[PDB]
């Protein structure tokens, strides 16, 4: 049974609610982004209308085989009518194709559903600027002040500089980057660009990347591993055993691996600056955990909410425990008292 925080009152609509069977009263299922916790339940046998971005619709058709007649892609930043209700899709600054959804209810209420997002001051100049929002359905993944991490640009600067230094010292070093979903493509693309290489990967991953409308992608990635000095592997393989095993397969072309695990936040963030990050090493293998986030920091979240000034907040993450819920409600009230709304 579908939980309340996935239902949009006053409409026939649900958000990210595909794992509950046929939801009573739902005439249109929105999908914010192509991450498995959110698409859970979708398949080629789905026969209701799914509304989403173009990129998400490429992935539904090619990876999950949803039939084309049920996929309804909408352009961003454009007022659209769906089943009698005005909606807008906004870039969520999450993974490729991820959106926030603005719903303009028939009774005059305006609802923003962030999906998963990384708040940014650039959102203060989208179509959000033009009117009041009554209810905010908020990605609260990192809603606690201990959650600090650097900008995505500082993280990429560290990775490029690290990779270019290592391979220039040793031209026989291979770079490996872990992945288990879409998002964080800038990590492996920026490293391959500095090294003058394409990124090598499995056929299944190449297919996924080909759905993402990235400019000049055919110039950047390949399935020919032998021709590439930046390889992508499943995240589960980014450990000393998996990397040893991979180095064997490269036929003595390489004698060292430098690997990257983009994580979200890890508690090494409470003490250490990005500049000061060091790897775990065993022999000729080094592994860096880098804090590349596609969710808001606590401070970025707070800034967005204090600018938006919603009348009510409904969290969509960390909702399963009473301690979590009570923590989040306390920060919402601080924020509102501090800013005066
Ligand atoms: Ni996500």
Image (cartoon, rainbow, N blue to C red):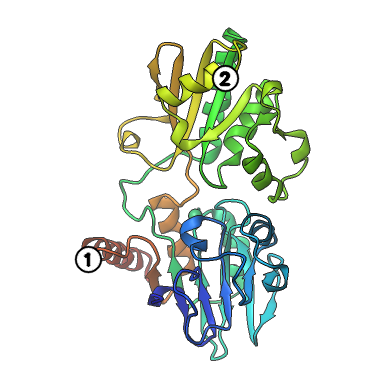
Residue 316 position within the rendered picture, expressed as x and y whole percent measured from the top left:
40, 65
Note whether ligand 1 is within 8 Å of mark 2: no
Dots 2, 1 in contact, CB < 8 A: no
Where's the C terminus, which quadrant? Answer: bottom left
Residue 114 seen: yes
Q: Secondary structure at mark 1?
A: helix
User: For the residues carrying marks 2 and 1, which lies nearer the camera in this image?
Assistant: 2
Relative horizontal placement of residue 190, taking residue 308 as reference (left or right): right
List the residue tagged with mark 1: 322
* Residue depicted at x 58% and y 32%: 232
Mark 2 or 1 closer to N-term?
2
196 above or below 235?
A: above
Residue 60 position within the rendered picture, expressed as x and y whole percent measured from the top left:
64, 60
Foreground: 340 or 10? 10
Residue 154 seen: no
Note whether ligand 1 is within 8 Å of mark 1: no
250 above or below 160?
A: above
- Which residue in the rendered view is the most extreme toward the bottom? 107
- Which residue in the rendered view is the most extreme toward the left? 323
185 above or below 281?
A: below
* Residue depicted at x 60% and y 70%: 45
Q: Residues within 10 Å of mark 1 (few under 14, many from 20)?
A: few
Foreground: 320 or 138? 320
Residue 31 position within the rendered picture, expressed as x and y whole percent measured from the top left:
56, 67
Q: Secondary structure at mark 2?
A: helix
Where's the N terminus, which quadrant? Answer: bottom left
* Number of on-image labels: 2
Residue 24 position within the rendered picture, expressed as x and y whole percent measured from the top left:
47, 85
* Residue depicted at x 56% and y 64%: 32
Query: For the residues marked 2 and 1, what is the alpha-carbon distance in whole angstroms?
Result: 49 Å
- Residue 216 has which mark? none
List the residue tagged with mark 2: 249
């Amino acid at each position: 049974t579908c939980p309340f925080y996935k239902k949009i009152p006053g409409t026939g609509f649900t958000v990210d609610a595909f794992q509950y069977g046929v939801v009573e009263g739902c005439t249109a299922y929105f999908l914010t982004h192509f991450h498995s916790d959110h698409y859970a339940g979708l398949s080629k046998h789905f026969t209701f209308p799914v509304y989403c971005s173009e990129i998400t619709g490429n992935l539904l058709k090619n990876k999950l085989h949803v039939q084309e007649q049920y996929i309804h892609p909408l352009p961003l930043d454009t007022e659209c009518i769906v089943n009698g209700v005005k909606v807008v899709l906004l870039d969520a600054n999450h993974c490729p194709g991820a959106v926030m959804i603005l719903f303009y209810l028939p009774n005059g209420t305006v609802i923003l559903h962030t999906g998963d997002f990384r708040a940014d001051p650039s959102m203060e100049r989208s179509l959000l600027a033009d009117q009041k929002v009554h209810m905010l359905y908020l990605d609260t993944t990192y809603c606690s002040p201990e959650y600090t991490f650097p900008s995505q640009q500082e993280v990429i600067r560290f990775a490029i500089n690290t990779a270019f230094e290592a391979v220039t010292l040793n031209p026989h070093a291979l770079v490996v980057c872990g992945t288990y979903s879409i998002g964080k493509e800038k990590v492996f693309l920026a490293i391959a660009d500095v090294l003058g290489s394409k990124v090598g990967m499995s056929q299944e991953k190449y297919k996924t990347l080909q759905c993402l409308n990235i400019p000049e992608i055919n110039s950047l990635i390949t399935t020919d591993m032998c021709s590439s000095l930046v390889h992508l592997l499943p995240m589960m393989q980014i450990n000393f055993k998996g990397l040893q095993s991979h180095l064997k397969k490269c036929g003595g072309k390489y004698n060292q691996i430098l690997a990257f695990r983009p994580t979200g936040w890890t508690h090494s963030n409470k003490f250490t600056r990005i500049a000061d990050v060091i790897p775990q090493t065993k022999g000729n293998i080094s592994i860096y955990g880098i804090p590349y986030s596609e969710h808001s920091s606590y401070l970025e979240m707070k800034r967005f909410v204090q600018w938006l000034k919603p009348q009510k907040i409904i969290p969509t993450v960390n909702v399963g425990t009473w301690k979590s819920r009570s923590t989040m409600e306390k920060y919402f009230r601080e924020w509102k008292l501090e800013a005066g709304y």
